[PDB]
Amino acid sequence: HMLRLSAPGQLDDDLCLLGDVQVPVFLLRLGEASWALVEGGISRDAELVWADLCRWVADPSQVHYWLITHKHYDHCGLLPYLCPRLPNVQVLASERTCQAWKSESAVRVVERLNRQLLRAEQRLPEACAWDALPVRAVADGEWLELGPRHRLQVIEAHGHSDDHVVFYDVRRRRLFCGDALGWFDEAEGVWRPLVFDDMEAYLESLERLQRLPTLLQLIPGHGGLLRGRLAADGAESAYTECLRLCRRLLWRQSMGESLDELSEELHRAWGGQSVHLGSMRRMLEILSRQA
Ligand SMILES: [Fe+3]
Ligand SMILES: [Fe+3]
Image 1 (cartoon, protein in one colour):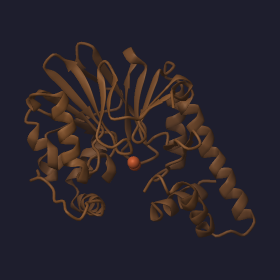
Image 2 (cartoon, helix red, strand yellow):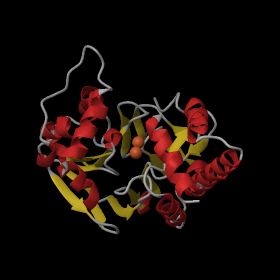
Image 3 (cartoon, rainbow, N blue to C red):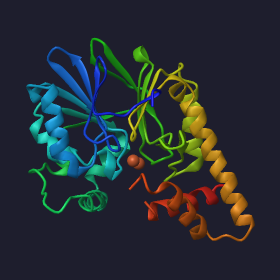
């Protein structure tokens, strides 16, 4: 499809997709000898992403920044395994996100969730400690002056998770929106809501994101790059789909349906491309809590 770039490699003059489109890691050419990464992947992809990186970047000492949208296992799983190979990298994440990496209970869930994704033959690279990562904490509204042509603004976007942020390149009308709009469904071309924390904050984040200057490029945490109207209308559409799901929880519960009976229907309907179910229930619980 032409409103959506989902192939590994070059997406724009300054931007490549590395690794798997479902859990991509984006690469920004900041300058002749200066690069940046955006989104932190899953752990098992450490060697794939590495191999993909080294095809665009001769010296990895040139990777200076790694931007992280939130703490979930599928958006920072690469950090302990590839940061040691990127000696000059500096990891930029929100205050709450950095605290997750200091929590031992939280780190243990990240590691366990990622380990369920390792293939039979494979083991992982040698790794940093999670509290040893070269990290600089960023705050809502901060400007990340990454290079002469790359200037991104950090925007708090809680709701998907209580730590979530997005990164706006206003020069390029390019939003790295993480999971804040949900999961884009390539089969039907609509967003699927990902509310795993607070529904009001999720809707409020989308309200603010809609007020951004018209997007040209919308880059979620999964699925690749969205352009044209998919980007322009992204935040409004995601907001709409979320409401749509609320009204359907309401409806089906007014007809005596358990959360599970709809947890199954939603898992059956969308879980064949985000492959969870236990996550699927905490969302339906969260939404039915606040309405
Ligand atoms: Fe997430
Ligand atoms: Fe995710």
